[PDB]
Length: 227
Image (cartoon, rainbow, N blue to C red; front, top):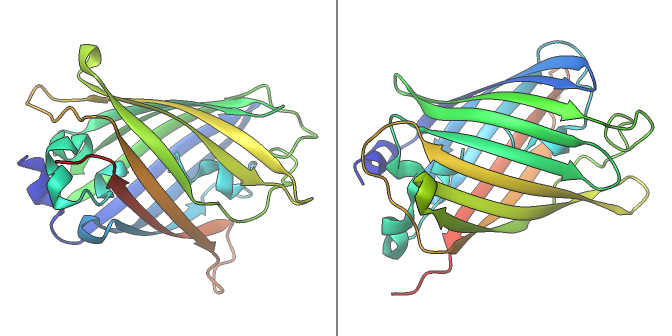
């Protein structure tokens, strides 16, 4: 795809999320760069409204799959880059086990030379005494795999997958993700055969940052199609 040519080097990234969870409003701003050749993303995020009212690990999947590494032999199955530069809409429901849910709608597109992810998030029916609003999750994210399928009627892709969040007592809380992506423009896109994305995430802190924040290193790589 011609969209793929936009990702052969290092691309600046901006992320802007406005959220409202049980009526608690917040904003997050992030900046960094993506290196799709290596499937690599480096970002720093700040809560620009003060204290983040949910744990940072619960927002990672919401806060740019066009930076996944698709191996050469799978290039015909990379929907996310093929929709560029006009971009795509990414929508999710995320259901937290024994707690509330997030609903998210985002647009991912180029604005000038920068790849921009702009998200609206709503969080509904959380327990003030639960792990999310009560901040009882560990500051990490386990590695996970997700199955991607084509949705030809909607000219995009779908994915359902579960994240296993670490709770500070040693237990695990499941976060069940329903995802759909649709192109914004009318040009041709690549609709893929079924395949997998594998993700690893490292979360850290900036020692000179006094605001509520997250430093993120993420790798995403595709697999599961044979010639």
